[PDB]
RNA sequence: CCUAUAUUCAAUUACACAACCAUGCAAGAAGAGACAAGUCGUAACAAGGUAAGCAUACUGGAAAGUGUGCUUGGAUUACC
RNA sequence: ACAGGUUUGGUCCUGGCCUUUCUAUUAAUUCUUAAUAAAAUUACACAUGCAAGUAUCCGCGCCCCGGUGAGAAUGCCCUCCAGAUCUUAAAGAUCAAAAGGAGCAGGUAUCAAGCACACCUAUAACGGUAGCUCAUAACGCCUUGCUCAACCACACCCCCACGGGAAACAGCAGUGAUAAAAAUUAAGCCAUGAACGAAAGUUUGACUAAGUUAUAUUAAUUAGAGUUGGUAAAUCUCGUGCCAGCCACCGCGGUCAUACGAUUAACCCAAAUUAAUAGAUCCACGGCGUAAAGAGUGUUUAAGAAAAAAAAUCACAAU
């Protein structure tokens, strides 16, 4: 089981910024950093390059990324693992139904 | 710092005060300074006699044997201290020095007897 | 470490190639490298003086290739020994010469590199090893009529004890260690010496590269 | 064991959610019943005015 | 200043101390280039003993000679400190009394 | 402080009093919640209060908050092994969310105690060195031993100058 | 190449080459301050004796004056 | 900050400067002995001495110790570790290059655009996409060793070190120049650390034991410095009279001085006392009608809060 990555970001979640690159996705991960003076948590953004072999990620997707065991280039060190929330087409994980924001597209109380 | 080579050595670091030595039995790299960076501290060694009159020496036998199994080299005074503690066999340098001291006492008493008559 | 403004140094890597080429092209041949001035005992190449304990032997004895230049096949299968071995060890210690490569640059031909089989204290080695300390002025050759008589060695078993008592504090450590778990056996603990066997300082070492297994 | 417990908890909460959503659907049906009977009144008055 | 603005601007840091006429040195060795008399400001009137020296840093500045009575001429080596004279505008240097060529004040005998 | 609705939550004591420590396999906590409706008051209060306490004790865990995409508030824990932990929070309260998280993925009291008992072993009482890592600087200051020469002057018999002077004659 | 090894090459080639700057000096120009002799007016502070000021334009030794909009950081003293 | 002095005929508020506390250097005055810690101007050039030896030859070490802070915003912390070294049959232990990143990281946005800094193919070659970073500060300029059991970088310079300037103390001592800055051109490996040798053992300007220095704390063999208008403890008598002169701020000098120079007296420190320069600390979790501040207006990107529920649209001079 010799499959290890030297990066700390073993698994990250971010929003897709741009898909201009072929088979490569540009994602932005937002973490919470404590201000040493204000003692408040603020959102720090960081851009990551990911390999999208199938080229299905569009602008506005919530994307999970796994650390690549070997970096293909000097800037791509992650791969698209799963799409969590497609833009405009959200599927509720708890109910398994399509939803449009706060409104249910298909009611779960009507199985048939 | 970066070194081309060297070996781990369990030795004595003179960290003390003027006319008042005090050694730290520590495992450190061979190419580092005496009072420089070390790996792990083991014990203490007190060269002066205290009020009660004992020479007080500390050994962390478990970590010492662990590091020595890992490949730590030893210095001669550390060997003398470990042999005196009973953890290791007596160093032959101590035995030959004791024999030399025996011969010095013998010649001293011989000269003292010959100078009196 | 790794920065965005790292300058691509090229002269530092060009100097590596230059020194690598100069190391082989200007390699000092072992003839002049091990040449010796017999009056001052001063090495002309390196600039070192010989130890004072080696002063008598240089003028009173000879090296390996100094006696090997008078043999027909450069000593194939011959036995060669050292006078230091003759003095210290009464048991026969010899080198079986299996191959020799003398230098052609020497104008008397008394320098070279030789391999062979080492038999120290009668113990024979079943492996091919390089002959160490060739330039030493201690080598001696045995004649053919004594080739068989020198090999005569009696195999006497050693009387070294196989187990020794532990030091006092360390022994008490085990006596307290097993007593806590409840071992009522009062057997005296021994320290093994089977794998503690070591070679003497007169035992030469191999000069071949170590293979990492 | 913990993850099976979490799955069971989520299924229980989903059952209570469905029970609540059916009552919400009934209340929504009541709202449709009132809005239809109103829009019948305002729709007819505009038709009479324009007629 | 909302919390977001405070986070964006960061904590306030005190500015570094600006160097004085001596460029951070407690004392400066100089040679007297012109000895003269300067007047104080409007509120008080006097005739102060002022000098113009060449500092070791190559800067030419005006200094004041404390004490009553002095014997300093051209090409005289003195030591100046960052003493500021309140009555004289622009004079921020004072010659140390008891130096190579500017000795202690003599008592009237 | 003074600015903010609840100045207390921006204090080191409040951040330290929240005891929720995740396991080594926990990597990502993705919270999804709504900003309307009475069902999600607990999720909104959780985001308002307990996120800083969890973040303070899990600095390497990435926590991301999302607003108004799913009608049902929930949490999604992404582990190292790839298993996704789905936690539905529809009517749970602020304290119930914390207790549920600690129950399903967290560290036991004994687990924390063993880690801190190991940590206290690193600083060793018998070692010597600086006051940051050791309790004693020079072994003179120990009561029973020879005093420090900078505090109590040593007798003439122990000074090195007298020993050289006697050897000179 | 009847035991096995030795030597060699890693030097050049085409173009901009003080442009860009940094530190002093400089024939000179202009500004600000302090203004120990002062000269010329009185612009502002009172409906400061033409109410002040803003933007802009023009004019005048000078404070400034005037035109067009704007403000009261001015009054109209209040059964007038 | 437990604060105080200081704007005005006067009060309140706002607001800056200074004083009161601690530390480090230099200068002045004074000075008696010891103990300990530290010796600090120079990356300007060096006369001379020593600082790498060990050993039956081979070999091993020979900026390792030690010295310095020029450059680098360098860097702090964290994963992986090639390679080197110790002992083993492997395996283990130390140093750990290179590659990076969850995060942190001097001033300057009057540095706002950088100008090739990106991706896929299958092979390590052809080609096709039009990309990549950046106001959450990219690309630039200036300054500086540092977050300290420590870490980073340098060894005369050209960032390197083939080559070119050119004959190297940024080793211990010492010498010129320079600077406000001033340790012995001295003894040893007895004890530690390092190197060598199987070893007795050798070397080590590292280190130890010392010589010099009020740079600092302690004991005493020692008593001098500062101040006496307010802040802030403490002045009697003489001389000058906006002159000489004094001061950290306010300020004082009238044949009218507890503030100038001298005497007496007094106060506070003390082998130290003042002056200067550096520091530690000190600005805003505070305000924006009149004191500095609501930007001439609306929309929108990025971003932020949707925390309990409601609403949208009517006479009159918008354009
Ligand atoms: Mg010392
Ligand atoms: Mg040698
Ligand atoms: Mg002054
Ligand atoms: Mg003097
Ligand atoms: Mg007018
Ligand atoms: Mg009028
Ligand atoms: Mg007028
Ligand atoms: Mg008029
Ligand atoms: Mg007027
Ligand atoms: Mg008026
Ligand atoms: Mg105007
Ligand atoms: Mg006109
Ligand atoms: Mg007109
Ligand atoms: Mg008015
Ligand atoms: Mg005023
Ligand atoms: Mg001095
Ligand atoms: Mg250093
Ligand atoms: Mg720079
Ligand atoms: Mg490794
Ligand atoms: Mg590394
Ligand atoms: Mg500018
Ligand atoms: Mg620097
Ligand atoms: Mg260099
Ligand atoms: Mg030099
Ligand atoms: Mg050197
Ligand atoms: Mg020196
Ligand atoms: Mg000199
Ligand atoms: Mg000094
Ligand atoms: Mg001098
Ligand atoms: Mg001197
Ligand atoms: Mg000596
Ligand atoms: Mg030694
Ligand atoms: Mg020795
Ligand atoms: Mg002192
Ligand atoms: Mg008088
Ligand atoms: Mg005075
Ligand atoms: Mg005073
Ligand atoms: Mg006086
Ligand atoms: Mg303020
Ligand atoms: Mg204003
Ligand atoms: Mg407005
Ligand atoms: Mg404006
Ligand atoms: Zn001590």
Image: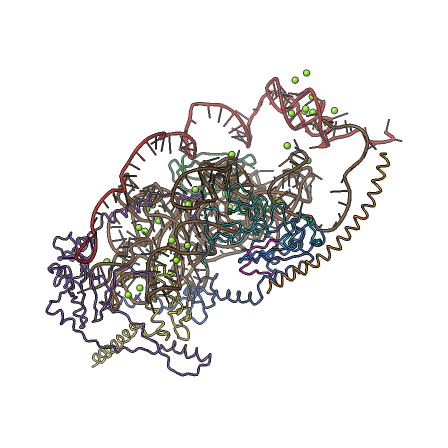
Chain colours: A cyan, B yellow, C purple, D orange, E green, F blue, G red, H brown
Position of the C terminus of chain B by quadrant: bottom left
The answer to whether H212 is drawn above or below residue E27 in the figure is below
Q: Nearer the viewer, residue F144 or H133?
A: H133
Q: Is residue F21 magenta?
A: yes
A17 drawn magenta: no
Counting labels gives 0
Q: Quadrant of ligand 9?
A: top right
H248 horizontally vs C99: left or right:
right
Q: Residue A9: x and y, percent?
A: 51, 53
Quadrant of residue H167 within the rendered picture: top left
Can you name the residue that lies furthest to the front here? A112
Quadrant in which the N terminus of chain B appears:
bottom left
Q: Nearer the viewer, residue E82 or C34?
A: C34
Task: Name the spot of residue H139 as percent of width and height, x first.
Answer: 47, 39
Q: Quadrant of residue D39?
A: top right
Quick check: A111 left or right of E38? right
Residue A18 sits above or below residue G47 on the image: below
Residue plotted at (68% across, 59% down):
D13
The reply to whether residue E104 is visible in this rendering is no
Q: Position of residue H260 (x, y in %)?
A: 51, 43
- In front of the other: H313 or C55: H313
E22 sits to left or right of H109: left
In this view, the residue in front, H276 or G27, is G27
The residue shown at (62%, 61%) is D6
| Magenta stretch, residue numbers | F19-30
Q: Residue at image x 36%, y 63%? A: B8
Q: Would residue C87 be found to the left or right of residue D26 on screen?
A: left
């Amino acid at each position: 089981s010799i499959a290890r990555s030297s990066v700390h970001a073993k698994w990250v979640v971010g929003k897709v910024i741009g898909t201009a690159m072929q088979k490569t996705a540009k994602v932005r991960v937002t973490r919470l950093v404590l201000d040493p003076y204000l003692l408040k948590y603020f959102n720090k953004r960081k851009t990551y390059f990911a390999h999208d072999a199938l080229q299905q990620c569009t602008v506005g997707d919530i994307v999970l990324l796994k650390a690549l065991p070997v970096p293909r280039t000097k800037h791509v060190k992650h791969e698209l693992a799963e799409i969590i929330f497609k833009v405009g087409q959200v599927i509720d994980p708890v109910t398994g139904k399509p939803c449009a924001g706060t409104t249910y597209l298909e009611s779960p109380i009507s199985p048939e | 710092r970066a070194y081309r080579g060297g070996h781990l050595t369990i030795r004595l670091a003179l960290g003390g005060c003027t006319n008042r030595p005090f050694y730290r039995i520590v495992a450190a790299h061979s190419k580092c300074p005496r009072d420089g960076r070390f790996v792990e501290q083991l014990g203490s060694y007190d060269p002066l006699p205290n009020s009660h009159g004992e020479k007080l020496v500390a050994l962390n036998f478990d970590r010492i044997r662990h590091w020595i199994g890992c490949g730590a080299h030893l210095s001669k005074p550390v060997e003398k201290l470990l042999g005196l503690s009973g953890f290791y066999p007596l160093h032959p340098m101590m035995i030959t020095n004791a024999e030399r001291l025996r011969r010095k006492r013998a010649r001293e008493v011989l000269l003292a007897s010959q100078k009196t008559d | 470490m790794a920065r965005k403004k790292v300058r691509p140094r090229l002269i530092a890597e060009l100097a590596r190639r230059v020194r690598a080429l100069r190391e082989q092209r200007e390699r000092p041949r072992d003839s002049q490298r091990y040449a010796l001035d017999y009056e001052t005992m001063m090495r002309p190449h390196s600039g070192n003086r010989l130890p004072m304990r080696a002063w008598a032997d240089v003028r009173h004895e000879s090296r390996l290739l100094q006696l090997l230049n008078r043999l027909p096949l450069f000593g194939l299968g011959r036995l060669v020994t050292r006078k230091s071995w003759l003095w210290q060890h009464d048991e026969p210690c010899y080198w079986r010469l299996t191959r020799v490569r003398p230098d052609y640059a020497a104008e008397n031909l008394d320098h070279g590199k030789a391999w062979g089989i080492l038999t120290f204290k009668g113990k024979t080695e079943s492996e091919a090893r390089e002959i160490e300390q060739v330039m030493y002025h201690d080598w001696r050759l045995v004649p053919k009529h004594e080739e068989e008589a020198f090999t005569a060695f009696t195999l006497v078993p050693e009387d070294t004890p196989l187990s020794v008592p532990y030091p006092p504090l360390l022994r008490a450590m085990i006596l307290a260690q097993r007593q806590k778990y409840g071992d009522t056996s009062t057997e005296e603990p021994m320290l093994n010496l089977e794998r503690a066997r070591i070679d003497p300082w007169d035992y030469p070492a191999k000069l071949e590269a170590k293979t990492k297994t | 064991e913990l993850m099976a417990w979490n799955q069971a908890e989520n299924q229980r909460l989903h059952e209570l959610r469905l029970a609540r959503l059916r009552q919400e659907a009934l209340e929504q049906e009541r709202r449709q019943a009132e809005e239809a009977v109103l829009q019948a009144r305002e729709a007819q008055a505009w038709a009479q005015l324009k007629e | 200043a909302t919390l977001n603005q405070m986070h964006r601007l960061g904590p306030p840091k005190h500015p570094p101390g600006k160097m004085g006429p001596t460029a951070g040195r407690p004392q400066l060795k100089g040679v007297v280039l012109r000895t003269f008399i300067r007047k104080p400001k409007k509120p008080n009137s006097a005739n102060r003993k002022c000098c113009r020296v060449r500092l070791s840093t190559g800067r030419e500045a005006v200094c004041f000679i404390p004490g009553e009575g002095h014997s300093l001429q051209e090409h005289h080596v003195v030591l100046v400190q960052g003493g500021r004279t309140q009555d004289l505008p622009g004079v921020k240097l004072t010659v140390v009394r008891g130096k190579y060529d500017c000795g202690h004040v003599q008592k009237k005998k | 402080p003074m600015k903010g609705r609840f100045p207390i939550r921006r204090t080191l004591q409040y951040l330290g009093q929240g005891d929720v420590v995740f396991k080594d396999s926990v990597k990502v906590m993705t919270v999804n919640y709504n900003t309307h409706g009475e069902l999600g008051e607990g999720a909104r209060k959780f985001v308002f209060f307990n996120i800083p306490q969890i973040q303070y004790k899990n600095p390497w865990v990435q926590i991301t908050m999302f607003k108004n995409m799913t009608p049902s508030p929930f949490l999604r824990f992404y582990l190292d092994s790839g298993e996704q932990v789905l936690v539905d929070v529809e009517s749970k309260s602020n304290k119930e969310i914390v207790e549920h998280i600690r129950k399903i993925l967290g560290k036991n009291e004994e687990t924390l105690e063993k880690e801190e008992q190991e940590k206290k072993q690193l600083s060793h009482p018998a070692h010597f060195g600086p006051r940051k890592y050791c309790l004693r600087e020079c072994m003179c200051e120990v009561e029973g031993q020879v005093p420090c020469p900078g505090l109590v002057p040593l007798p003439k018999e122990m000074t090195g100058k007298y020993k050289a002077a006697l050897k000179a004659t």
